[PDB]
Image (tube, coloured by chain):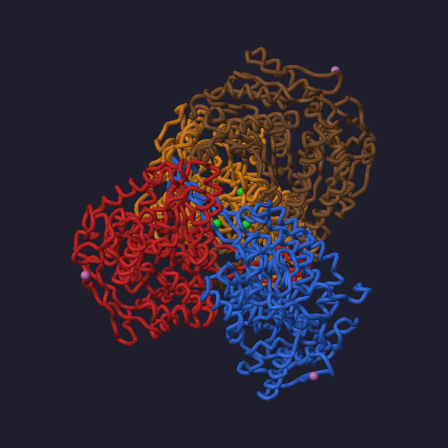
Chain colours: A blue, B red, C orange, D brown
């Protein structure tokens, strides 16, 4: 784990449009904070409807027929993306520090996991650019028919604060690989890494207007994107609540395409025959990773009666081993929550757990004199009606439940409007296949949890999302199919 | 062209749920009319929110893990669909008569085109049932990862009145092939063919609750479908205006998946080098087919200056050759519009053409003492600002425009919020490919128009739709991808 | 199990070319026998090089550009195949009787398994006809590039005697679905079902010359096919020995494409944790099905030491329960071997088992006064060097071996030039996945054996074959890819 | 066009096995020559059957289950290939010089075309590594079935002398991307670039034994590869004559898979309406590129009568503009033929053209006092029976023929056992599509010629080849499909 041997200096704080740095039309700025100290890190230009309009015009112009981005070889789009990955690799130390400092993310994770995933995902996407293909089709009658899988056009992309850099790349990688242009609105909490990446997009040689980055707030800049009459598609990751507003606004405006990656209340099912230590470790990591600030948090763990007490005991032992503090210090194993609103919501939910009669096993309160820290918390004897069993906590709070009937626990696992992911722990082949088939979740892990790679599509069932990101399948939502049918004198097979 | 040698008797008029016939919960009925005579044909049970709720419960139960529809071989779903096609083929005379009588559709077309397309499309879809496949994926790390392309679940399907039988099959064929269950709401104007098909679904042996058909009105039964908290996906074909309401309601309710096939204002571009007679014939058929009541109507025809006068002349000659009347009588070549609302809208638009200074070449008024008939109408010297150049008419009204610059005419062709289809007429290879690439339309025909087959995906760019129907690509919107990732000791390529 | 209530009458005995029945050019005929009685059933026209030449000219003419088979809609090729399946279904009783009588196949199996598989496979293939698609490709430079997946042309298809009807359809179904024309040479032992099917091909309405059937001998008619200068592809199922001659002759003649489905010496690995009764039953059925006359016979069963004695005991109990006799009589559970040569080879191999010191558990000799019957035979304590452990027996002879080390048994399983299939019996998820990955076999069954369906590709590793049949992947070997690259002024994504 | 500013020094001349440099088992060496001067460049170790055996053992060991190459992430195989491309890019000057000096290839072409194509193709292949996917399949019955697209194993790859570096990468790129190990035998005329690349394979960090390079002769080392009992697949590019021997030897040995890219006698058809200057230029470049030493040489140009004289005139003008000499000197536009055998064959064929009565328009003899130079030669009034119209010349010799009937000229174009490529020159959409459909050739160019890219599959019909290289489709011949079918209690869609 190497480190940045010089203090981090912030440089890019302006709106990025047509590969140039712009002040906001209003001239207004907004503060960016460090969640571990509660102090301001810098001021960033506040983009609003006027700044989004400017970005969309730039993206539209870069998408015009005959433009450099439209006419360059698909393989050259791929080359630009591979170059961008090499540049992010070059700036790995500074990006990981910036991510840790701005996002409250453990530095070891930011460096070893987030930045590695960013680079790997970009390289994966670069490889697809010249492999996106349409079809020739044996239509009835004397015609030659083919399809083009064209880019859609201008894509508005709203990035969350939990994995700012990784999610930036999950959105721009496929969009750019397919030949779209983008208007990106990073989270108001975490715009800094995106703006540094914008500097590298310019350096890599992307044509101007292909990527535009407008920092600002959700209700202003985000709503402007979702309601814009000349944005062809919006991609959003965040709360199911905002996802509903995005989908509504797309309908009311211009029927723009929508992909959504939203909340979860993901279940694990631990059968009596499971490797118990493996299940305890993965379920733990599943819920506590990045201070519980993952959509796929394993937030309902159902364990068969006969191993339930042992599971809870081993779980509690594991949860008591954390060292809270500044995420930049080596040996620290839990950072802060992102901000006050999230912090408040987590404490309010923990209070309902206590009140509604869940058994508190450890934690259950705040920590420290500054920073938005929550003690890692475990609740056992949780029942399905409790707030902590129904609502996404997005904090370091583990719920452990008991079951005796597999039919019943699958019904309980599925009894939610969420459906992002699930885990199944068992040594039985038949159970692994049949339970994973029966769970209403977009990703099911068997004897593991939280394994996400560029090669696999990822997305939710039900209210956890619309569409998929990554893998071969995820590229589909960044193309628009055009059928061309040509009259011919005589067709032959 | 054989005919039904006995008078048509109407039999199926009730709500179809769990393969049984139900009265409406309210007990209310609504009238169904013949648009050629303005007389009532029968009374049909009026489904509302209570009847939709009943249908969705039935569809949900038929979709449960372990149910007959979920556990039967994919190849058996295909067999049921091929059986259903054979039954529709058996009842071809009666279905085509019912379609002609109820829908105002020329009988020769209903028999030779609509019913043939219904049967062919069903047979095509039947063939896909056991060919829908997921992937095994070479994920990073020691894991085995695969995907399942599962059915989504309960699909609400809202069918238009213009092609009631064909569009019923375009929706149910793929949905059922993929293993979904469906709640169908046929158009209030045209429920009769759908209910007859329901009788054949029962006869073919589909399990109960797999297909449920609830006749009724858009604002009541349609809104109930779009806003239902346990419908996983809604598919709608109709006006862009209603499409916007559907997408809004999906967002506000349960974030259900939405596919929309909506209006158009589709352009044709006729180059000076085109086979003129071929272009005149296809552009004519393109706009006048089924009394102009096609989403893909070729409603803006741009013709190069030097051949423009000849094109208009030959167009007018062709448009003056129709015989209006009852669509059941042999030799009749134009039937009525579907209803009063459509009729009014068409006459009001024709009035704006005259008023705003378009040149009326033929037609321009109503016809007859009964039935919703409009004279076939041609306007030349149309300009881009006129109501008839901007708004979907959905009537027998042809607009012919002049151009001299190809750059300019592509911009004019694309200058609309619509984007369903387009036509290009030229003998030049380079022009055919480059113009078709530049047009923002889901289907582009070259030297033809209106060629639609089961093998080709069909759908709109921009506000003409979201998603695609038919072809390999159209099956994607009736599946939900689940990724399963299994921990293993050691992976090998 | 219904039966033919009238004595079977043989009708079609001539060469089938251009949908007409031909005598042999020489005028010669050859006898066809019943293997259960050793008596002649009829005389069939003996096709030779002159008759193959005539068939290839017919197939070539039916494949010419502009011919009915080349110009008909892909969907119509599919319709013809679905019609042919309906006709085979209609003649199911007579075909199953003919198969049983001619092939020595148990009637219950012929009716319930072979004929059902024939019909299902044809219906599967029919579904692919209009779903075979090429690609549009984003090539570097200003070009439009697409591919056509064309039929190859005239395909010579050499069918084995073990599953004459099923294998006829495995070859012609995909070939015809893809738009090829075929010259078929059924096994000299079993030409009768193929000729009846030819009568149904004519009845279904296939254009003449699309399917031609030339009965005759391997060294004459088969060699003529393999060495023909105007056959584009040869498909052969049979012994690895003949497969080598076919591949050699394709190289020496016209470099025709070759697919081969050849012998096996397929292993099963039974782990100590396996469901023992399930493993015993599947391994038994795996080796004894159709008198052991299956390429995939489970002819080396490796069982973990601790359950080995119990496995052998339960295996022997199962093998002693057969009733030998005429395959048409209800209750009979083992028919004869196909002919003298196979019969001799089986007895000679059984003699080596005894001689080389394998432990004979049951059987080990001939049965009856007529017909080519072999007692069902089990050998335990078999070692890897014995003839019965190395050579394909193609008879009712089970070999059971012991192992203690999983590493070692995988090496033993793989230590063969064969590689058609394998079985793994275990309750452990990790073992199932890792063992199946490590086995060098085209199909690996887990906790089952011999499960073959139209939807799955099937074929060998190593000397068990070249290429795959059936599934999506199997259709590839019946197309030829043509790339078309068109110069254009300017490409756009 | 930058150049190597230091004299080229040859370094790598030994056999490359397990990432180490080996002398030949015999200790023998063979000379390598410069074809422009006829002088020896160096001595290289002569690999024979003993050296191939050593290479195959190394490749087999690197392919064992549990080895680094088998267990590394697919994405890491891709990374190694992208690294190798970066290294070839770094050594571009030296590789292009070595190619020019050893291969007789014009330096500008070697640098700007060959090396660029090498790098681009490697980068394309790198992108596929983690995108090779199998399927999950909805089989009949209660089973879970999936497929693995595994690497085949040890691939023997025999590279031609005409494009030594490009063809090396066309073979190793896909093979390695798919996870195979390789034993490569470069052409005896041109081993030097391959051995330098081997040095870069070691530097990039490929595991030992994954790539092994054995220089030597065709009849010894090549035959050893083709006949080896433990090589799973052989890929060969070269003469159709040797291709036949390779396919024969694969059949006689171990039924190894064979892909062949062989000769051509490719036709162009120039219609009267074609852009004549464009057609003349592409047809010229098509036949004369790299001294005519391309499999796809446009060696039969059929031109419509009315433009034939003008075409010949303009062709002859173009062919008279070459400057022959050493391919390293700027401004030189034609290098030597590769060796004496090729040189002799070309002069002998040119002599038949004169003798059999073709009209000699220019050239027709040798050039210079040293080097294997042939004057660029044009023959008009060529007829279909002449040796120069039937046999692959593989030299700078253009044949121009006359036609009047399009039906007849397509028959003439197709009347050959070859089928690699073809060109069609016309402005007519219908003709372009229908002629390209009717030509029996693997690649058809329209209004261009010789356009080859990594994204497009390439290969022959008929005796010009078996299989395809490059594009998505070309990756298929470097995988082996394994079906895994798992018994389950109950399947659900
Ligand atoms: Cl498509
Ligand atoms: Cl997928
Ligand atoms: Cl392809
Ligand atoms: Cl597959
Ligand atoms: Yb505080
Ligand atoms: Yb009226
Ligand atoms: Yb005997
Ligand atoms: Yb000389």
Residue B432's spot in the image, x, y percent?
45, 40
**Viewer can see residue C9:** no
Residue B392: horizontal and vertical position, in percent? Answer: 35, 56
Residue situated in front as seen by the camera: C420 or B261: B261
Which sits in the foreground, C325 or A194?
A194
**Left/right of residue C149 with respect to residue C212 in the rendered view:** right
Q: In the rendered image, which quarter is residue D230 located in?
A: top right
- Give left or right: position of C232 versus D101: left
Residue B136: name its quadrant. Answer: bottom right
The residue under the point 60% across, 52% down is: A177
Q: Nearer the viewer, residue A118 or D236?
A: A118
Using the image, determine if residue C118 lies above or below residue D103: below
Q: Is residue A238 above or below residue C246?
A: below
Q: Position of residue A87 (x, y in %)?
A: 72, 55
Quadrant of the frame with the N terminus of chain C: bottom left
D139 to A165, vertically: above or below:
above
Q: Could you tell me how many numbered marks the image carries?
A: 0
> To which quarter of the image does residue A402 belong?
bottom right
Query: Where's residue B232, x and y in %?
Result: 45, 67
Residue D368 visible (yes or no): yes
Q: Residue at x 50, y 58 (%)?
A: A232
């Amino acid at each position: 784990l190497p480190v940045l041997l010089t203090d981090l200096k912030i440089q890019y704080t302006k709106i990025f449009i047509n590969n140039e740095w712009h002040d906001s039309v209003s001239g207004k700025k907004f503060p960016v904070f460090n969640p571990a100290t509660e102090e301001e890190l810098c001021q960033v230009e506040e983009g609003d409807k006027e700044d989004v309009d400017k970005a969309v015009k730039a993206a539209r112009q870069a998408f015009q027929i005959g433009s450099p981005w439209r006419t360059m070889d698909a393989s050259e789009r791929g080359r630009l993306l591979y170059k961008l990955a090499d540049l992010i690799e070059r700036d790995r130390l500074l990006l990981a520090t910036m991510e840790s400092m701005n996002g409250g993310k453990l530095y070891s994770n930011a460096y070893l996991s987030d930045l590695a995933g960013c680079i790997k995902t970009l390289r994966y996407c670069a490889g697809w650019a010249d492999k996106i293909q349409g079809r020739t089709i044996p239509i009835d009658g004397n015609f030659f028919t083919y399809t083009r899988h064209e880019p859609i056009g201008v894509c508005g992309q709203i990035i969350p604060w939990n994995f700012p850099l990784v999610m930036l790349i999950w959105k721009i990688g496929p969009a750019l690989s397919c030949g779209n242009t983008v208007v990106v609105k990073p989270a108001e909490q975490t715009p800094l890494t995106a703006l540094h990446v914008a500097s590298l997009i310019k350096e890599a040689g992307f044509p101007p207007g292909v990527v535009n980055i407008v920092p600002g707030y959700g209700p202003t800049a985000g709503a402007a994107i979702s309601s814009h009459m000349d944005i062809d598609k919006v991609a959003f990751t965040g709360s199911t609540e905002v996802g509903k507003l995005i989908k509504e606004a797309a309908g009311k405006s211009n029927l723009k395409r929508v992909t959504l990656e939203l909340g979860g209340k993901s279940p694990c099912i631990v059968l009596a025959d499971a490797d118990l230590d493996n299940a305890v470790e993965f379920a733990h990591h599943g819920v506590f990773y990045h201070q519980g600030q993952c959509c796929i948090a394993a937030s309902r763990i159902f364990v068969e009666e006969s191993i339930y007490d042992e599971f809870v005991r081993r779980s509690v032992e594991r949860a008591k081993k954390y060292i809270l503090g500044n995420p930049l210090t080596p040996g620290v194993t839990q950072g802060p929550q992102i901000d006050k609103e999230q912090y408040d919501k987590i404490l309010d939910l923990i209070e309902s757990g206590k009140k509604e009669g869940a058994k508190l096993e450890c934690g259950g309160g705040p920590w420290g004199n500054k920073g938005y820290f929550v003690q890692p918390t475990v609740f056992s004897n949780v029942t399905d009606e409790m707030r902590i069993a129904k609502e996404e906590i997005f904090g370091p709070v583990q719920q452990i439940m008991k079951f005796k009937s597999l039919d019943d626990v699958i019904k309980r696992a599925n009894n939610t409007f969420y459906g992002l992911s699930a885990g199944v722990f068992t040594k039985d082949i038949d159970k692994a296949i049949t339970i994973s088939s029966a769970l209403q979740a977009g990703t099911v892990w068997v004897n593991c949890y939280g394994v996400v790679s560029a090669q696999c599509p990822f997305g939710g069932f039900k209210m956890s999302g619309n569409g998929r990101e990554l893998g071969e399948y995820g590229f589909h939502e960044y193309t628009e199919v055009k059928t061309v049918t040509v009259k011919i004198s005589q067709k032959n097979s």
